[PDB]
Every structure is written in C-alpha cells, then in structure tokens.
Amino acid sequence: IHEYLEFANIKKTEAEKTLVDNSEKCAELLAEILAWDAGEILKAASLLGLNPPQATNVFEIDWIRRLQTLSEKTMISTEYLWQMGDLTENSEFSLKEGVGEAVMAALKAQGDSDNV
Amino acid sequence: SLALLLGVTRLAVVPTNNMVTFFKGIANGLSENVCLTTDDFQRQELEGADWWTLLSTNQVIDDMGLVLDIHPVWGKSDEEMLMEKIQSIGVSNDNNTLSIIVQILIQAKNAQENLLSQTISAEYGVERSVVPLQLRWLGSNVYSVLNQVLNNTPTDISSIVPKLSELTYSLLIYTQLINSLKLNKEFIFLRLTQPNWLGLTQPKLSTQLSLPEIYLITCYQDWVVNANKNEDS
Amino acid sequence: SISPRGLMKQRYQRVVTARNASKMNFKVPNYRFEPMLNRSKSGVETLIQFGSTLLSLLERKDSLSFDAYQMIQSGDLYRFSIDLQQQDIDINKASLE
Amino acid sequence: SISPRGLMKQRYQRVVTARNASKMNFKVPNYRFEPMLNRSKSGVETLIQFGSTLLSLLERKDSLSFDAYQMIQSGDLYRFSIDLQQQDIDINKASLE
Amino acid sequence: QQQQAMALLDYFSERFTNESLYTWLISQLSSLYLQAYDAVLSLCLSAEA
Amino acid sequence: SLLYELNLGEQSFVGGGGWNDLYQGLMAGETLKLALMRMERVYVEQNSR
C-alpha cells in the first residue's frame, strides 16, 4: 500500500499528469492489491480534472471498498451505477426506461436458480 | 497462475527506489571489511590484485593464466575441480606452492557467494541452499549481479539496467515455480547439469519452460513419493 | 444446505532488511599498544554479557505475557456454555407439564 | 462394509556420510613458540563460543517456527465443523413443520 | 472459537521475540564465524613452524 | 597506538556506527572482538628488528 501511494504522488505537474501517470500500469496495482478488475475501475476518469485519478490518497479506495461489496450484492457494473446517479434530477426519460430494463435483465441472468 | 508461470499475458511492476536501497545494501555488504578478490575476477591474466603481493614469499604469480570460475556438475563439483583447472594450465611447479594457493582461495570464493545466499533469502523467503541454483536456473551469474555495483547501480537515480530491473521481476515468477509446488535441490542440480541426460530436448538448455516438462517433472515429483523406498535409490 | 464459505489463506511472508551503514576514525595515542590490548578485552566481553542478559531476560518477559493472555480466552466460553445449557432445566419442567 | 485400507508404513531410515578430507602445510616463523601459545588460545575458544551461539540460536529459531505452523492446522477444521453442524437448525425447523 | 483462535495467531505473530529476531541475529552471526575461521589458523600454523 | 608504534599506513579496523535502533544495540559488541582479531594479526606479522 505504501509503494502504491508513493508512486501515485510522483510529480503530477512537472511530469506525470500529461503522461496520464502511465494509466495502463499505475491503475493496475490499485486493482491488484484488491485482487479485483483492472478494467471498470478506469471509470474513475469521469471525475477529478483529467487525472487517472489516483493521487487522492484515500477516498477512491474508500469508495471502491463499497463498489466491491455492491458488486457482490448484485452483478451490475459501476458504469450502470453511475446512471443510477445521473437519473436523480428530473433527468431525460429514455435513460430510466433503459436502466430499469437493464437491471431486470441482470436479475434474469441469476433467476430462481443462482447462475451469474 | 499456470498462464503467468508459462509467461503468457505477463505481470506489471514499478521500479521503486527501494530497489536502489537494496542494491546499495549489497554494495555496502561487499565493501565493509569483506575485502573481496572480485577485482576483475575471471578474465585471463588476472594482474595487479592485492592478495598474492602480501603472500609473495610463498607464491608471486598473481596474474596466473586462464580463468578462475566454475560451472556445476552432478555427483562431485567442489574445490577439486577448481584445483584441477588451475593445475591443468601449464604449472610445472606441482609442489606445495600450487596446493597452498587453493586453500588460500576457498574462503575468497565463499566471500563472493555467501553475500547473495545470506541476503536475498531475507527478501524473498527461500533457504540459503537453494539461492545460487535458483539464480543460475533463472538465467544469471553471481559475478554478473555483483558487477552491477561497478555499473553504478547504487546511484539513487530512478533508473537501473534491464539486467537487474527485469531479472528482479523474473525472480518472482521463478519463486512461484518453487512454492506453488515444493521440490528439493538435487532435482534442480541434475536439471541444471545435464538436461538431455535427465530426459529433455536440446533447446531446453535455454531458460524457457513449457507444458511437456511441467507434466513430466510433476509426475516425477509424485512418483518419488509414491515409490516403495526412500529418496536416493 | 446450499453454500460453503472462504478461509484464512494466512500464507504471507515478512521482510527483514539485512544491510548496514558505517563511518571513519582519527585520534592520536598517548601510551603503548599492548597495555591497551590488556584493557580493551574485558569491557567488550562485559557488553556481550549485558547484551545476552538483556536478550535472555526479554525471552522470559515475552513468554510469560503469552501464558497470561491465554487464560482470559475461557471467559466468553463459560458465559455461552451456561446460557445455552440452562434451558435444559426449563425443558425438563416443560416435559413434566 | 466390504473392505479394509492400507497404512503409512513410514519406517525408512536416512544416511549420514561420516567421513572427511584434508591438506598439508608449510610456512617459516618470525618470533618464538610460547608467545604464540599465549595468543592462539583465545581466538580459537571465541570460535567455540560463536559456533555454540549460532547452534543454540538456530534451535530457538526452528523451535518457534514449529509453534507458528501448528496454529493454522485449526482453520479447515472450523470450516468443516460449522458447515456440518449448521444443518441441525434446518432439521429443527423441518421437525417443527 | 474460530475468531479468537485467529486473534491468538495475531497476538503470537505480533510478539516482539517472534521468528524475525532469531533470523536477524543468525543471518549476521554467520559472517562473524567465517571472518574469524579464515583468520585464526595462522596462529596455530605459526606455532608449528 | 598500533599505527604510530609500528609507523604504519592506514587499515581502518574500528569503523563507527555499529549501534542499531530497530533492535536496541543487539550484536554491537561481537564486532569489536573481530576488530581486535583483524588488528592483532598486523602485529603478528609486522614485528622484526
């Protein structure tokens, strides 16, 4: 955890931010310490100023704890959990009509059996 | 795990400056009173090295001739091969002046090996009897690692040679090859000595590994336990 | 009867940093060499005696602190044992009814 | 009820090669015999002290590593104990039905 | 019982004189013995001479 | 005193910094025995009329 956080903090303005921190391998170790998916964690690039983002040294890990447990309550993606936020504010209707159907299909994929 | 061990879709790692603290630790351990004879160690005409200048009343010829280094072989390696190699290279003075400079050299060879076998055992969790065999079977040499001190590896720039930075990465995968299954050094010693004699094909003198070995060495590692008599028969 | 459970995969190692650092010396003498060899020994070997005294006492300290903490492990088990078993008096009364 | 089974016939010995090898000496002296008997002793007996220190510490090392590995032997047994016994709640519910 | 057996393994593995201290002593002392052994033998050899 | 009384060039046996602050000075005395052994052997050789 220390070697990961020390690497995340290296020289954002003078070097690493415009080089995307080498996102393809720095964001990999954040998945590896969790034994988790190095893929969908890259959705974090939807916030924090075009950084990876990773140098916010706790809150992203603290949230990913809850994303990992939610990802074991249900087989839904973090990509769809973002839409469940976007729909809050009297938002566009076709996204709600689609998200309801997508969650229904994600339940059929488990059914009265167990499956995945 | 098997795909990683077979080298398909390989791992990623960060060159943290802690690695320099480790290699500077090796350089420090080499420098603090070990006083090692590694000063241009192998290559022919070994001239200008301190140790035999002091002992010159007993023997002068510090330059010797051909090289002072060893490759392992089964049944019996040891200082008898190091003696026979230096005895073969045209010394006509077969008296005690030749044998005394072998018993002066044995502890000086130990002082090159004992550094790695005692230190890296505390980094990676392997017994000191496995370390030099693991190092060669990975595709390395004890002096080639120690020469990286002379290549300025102890300098705390955030860059080091691939010969260390990818070797260190490769050591972890070969550590899982000796912990996801456990086996004894005599197997490694045979495998490293004589691949075709063990039963492999000539290309497997290289560092590369594939499933036709992994089946046979695993089914051997079962059969050596399953057999009705102890280890050595 | 539908599910297994995970385990304590408690296999992980820990690392000891086997390396050193050190510094140089100077000074000028005031009397002979062998008279100092006849004084330096006993002060050094007394430090080996003090260091092995400290080490061997610290094993005696940290051994007995384990023997202490191992006793209190029974305290919850007595509570759970009584508060499970006491119901067999109430069952033996319910059987009489 | 038709068959027995084999056993661990774990009787086999192991062999220790009790033999040696050794080499000759030369050199020429620079000062007297008894002054060297008055120096050679303490360096040798310090090596007996270092060797017995190494040996007695290595017993303390390899003893405590056994006490460690002996604890994790409980981890599977708790898993199997819970995943066998938990069914008696489901049987006590099936008996109420 | 399972969780306090895990807490005993934690309390044991967080003991001061755990496996690391004997390992650290021996892995240094192994050098002190060899640095003495390669040096002492000239005293008894010069006693013969 | 050795290097003055024999009038000799540098050999630096007594290196400073042998204390330890993870392990509170353990083994910081046994090194002094080996320093005296490395030192004594200069006197075993380098004395003559």
Image: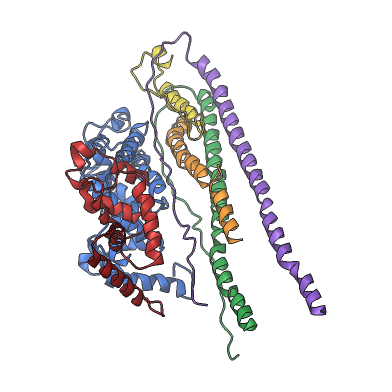
Chain colours: A red, B blue, C purple, D green, E orange, F yellow
Please state the horizontal and vertical placement of residue E13, each as a whole percent of the image: 53, 49
Q: Which quadrant of the view contains residue D68? A: bottom right
Q: Which part of the image, by quadrant, shows the C terminus of chain B? A: bottom left
Q: Which part of the image, by quadrant, shows the N terminus of chain B? A: bottom left
Report the side of B203 relative to A64 (left or right).
Answer: left
Q: Which of D96 and D85 is in front in this view?
A: D96
For the question of whether residue B122 can be seen, the reply is yes
Please state the horizontal and vertical placement of residue C18, each as a whole percent of the image: 41, 40
Report the side of B139 relative to B103 (left or right).
Answer: left
Report the side of C83 relative to B13 (left or right).
Answer: right
Q: Which quadrant of the view contains residue E5? A: bottom right
Q: Nearer the viewer, residue F35 or B26?
A: B26
Name which residue lies at 56% across and 83% down: D5
Residue at the left extreme of this rendering: A18
Q: Is E37 situated above or below C97?
A: above
Q: Nearer the viewer, residue B13 or C25?
A: B13
Q: Nearer the viewer, residue B43 or D93?
A: D93
Number of numbered discs visible in the structure rendering:
0
Residue at the top extreme of this rendering: C30
Residue at the right extreme of this rendering: C96
Q: Is B217 situated above or below D4?
A: above
Please state the horizontal and vertical placement of residue C15, each as a whole percent of the image: 42, 46
Please state the horizontal and vertical placement of residue B121, each as a whole percent of the image: 40, 48
For the question of whether residue B45 can be seen, the reply is no
Residue at the front extreme of this rendering: A90
